[PDB]
Amino acid sequence: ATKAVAVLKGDGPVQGIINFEQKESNGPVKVWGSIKGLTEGLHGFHVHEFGDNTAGCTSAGPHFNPLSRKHGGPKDEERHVGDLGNVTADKDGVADVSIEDSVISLSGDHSIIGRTLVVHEKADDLGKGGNEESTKTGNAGSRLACGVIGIAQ
Amino acid sequence: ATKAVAVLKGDGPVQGIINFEQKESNGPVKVWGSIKGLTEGLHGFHVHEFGDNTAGCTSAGPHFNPLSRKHGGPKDEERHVGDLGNVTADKDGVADVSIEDSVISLSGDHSIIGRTLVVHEKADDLGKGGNEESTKTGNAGSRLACGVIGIAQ
Ligand SMILES: [Cu+]
Ligand SMILES: [Cu+]
Ligand SMILES: [Zn+2]
Ligand SMILES: [Zn+2]
């Protein structure tokens, strides 16, 4: 492995198309991507525990990451194992993602392949809710659409 | 892991909800479940290598298996790896899947978690179609709908 993509879907217009590429195993994974079909503003963007989708973008789980610290993101140290957090969709629903992370592993041990990328309706609290949800998905609301990665190359 | 799924979809009516269970990491991966939404008769069913779905069930790799031999099936020895043969849909558009991939494993070395499942428009010739496509994907034709393997246990 070296390049990974997840295509997200659920609502229909909301089609996500992430690109997690590791230039090397010693390179941070640049977790870039291009969702379209959403409404404006920041949206829920995270990892979730299970890759599973049997219930329809739900069974996937809450953010039951092993290093259970606090729901945060690239804004926190406490971040779960792939809280991108809050990424902004244009008026067109076009959310460009271009962040890089030195925590996850495309392949290795963590093998962040059979995970469920979820696009949520709302922005997360990035932990600040001070609610049970706040330490889990923040306050992102439901999973609108979701996708499994599956490696690219 | 021990339990994984693959939710296939593309068209909308057509969706699979396949359950991959390996009792151990070295037991048979019994891949069971069903695709609902098909039309009657035999249909495309394989395990494509790349997760990649960026183009829409198109780019996922025309069976880029390691044991590059022939597109075959449980009819042939020379089968790529996850050439299921053919899944046959009832009149209701319900095709049962219930096979043991008594070959590969979800985790360990073979680690098929991540691979992409595709339901096709037409039946597989299983190599003996006599076209490049017979030997590549079984002449099974248009990849109506597809899904990516994700862990559930
Ligand atoms: Cu999420
Ligand atoms: Cu296929
Ligand atoms: Zn989180
Ligand atoms: Zn094949």
Image (cartoon, coloured by chain):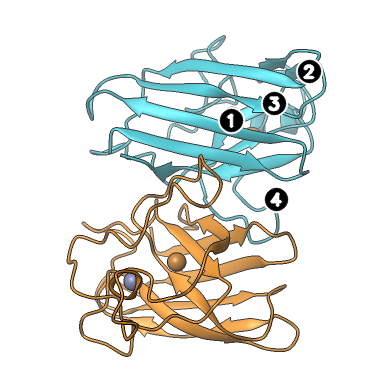
Chain colours: A orange, B cyan
Q: Which amino acid does label 4 sit on?
A: Thr
Q: Is mark 3 within 8 Å of ligand 4?
A: yes
> Could you tell me which secondary element the residue under label 4 belongs to?
loop
The answer for how far apart the CA atoms under marks 2 and 3 are is 24 Å
> Could you tell me which secondary element the residue under label 1 belongs to?
strand
Q: Tell me if mark 4 has few (under 14), some (14-19) or many (20+) residues whose alpha carbon lies within 10 angstroms of its own.
A: some
Q: Identify the mark at residue A91; answer none if there is no mark.
A: none
What is the chain letter for disc 4? B
Q: Do the residues labelled 3 and 1 touch (CB within 8 Å)?
A: yes
Q: Do the residues labelled 2 and 3 touch (CB within 8 Å)?
A: no
What is the chain letter for disc 3? B
Which picture quadrant has residue A105? bottom left
- Find the residue positioned furthest to the top: B75
Measured from the top left, where is residue A47 in percent x and y? 39, 64
Q: Do labels 2 and 3 share a chain?
A: yes
Q: Does the residue labelled 1 lie within 8 Å of ligand 2?
A: yes
Q: Mark 4 points at which residue?
A: B58
Q: Tell me if mark 3 has few (under 14), some (14-19) or many (20+) residues whose alpha carbon lies within 10 angstroms of its own.
A: many
Q: Tell me if mark 1 has few (under 14), some (14-19) or many (20+) residues whose alpha carbon lies within 10 angstroms of its own.
A: many
Q: What residue type is labelled 2?
A: Asp
